[PDB]
Image (cartoon, rainbow, N blue to C red):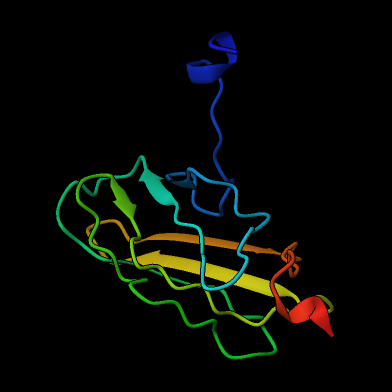
Length: 127
């Protein structure tokens, strides 16, 4: 529907009223080492070249380990390429995500909720 294309949009509510994530990773779809990449939108003062870092480990566990999680904000937006997504998937565990940027007006952005990622149908299910 071309009418519901540009008119609507998708963002994640974060603790900071200036930092918003364009994609809604409330879910995930990785058959294997196939992660998803999102961009961060910031309405704060930060058009210079800074750094955005993100993690996704459970509070009772280490912080998840992502690759290329330190992208340089170009303007008010950043993006992750080789983003590797390998955080623990314990469903009974609380999943915690935290994003911090140290430019001129340090914006804090975190997201904490359960994770909806499960094995899709690789070749291991054969046993």
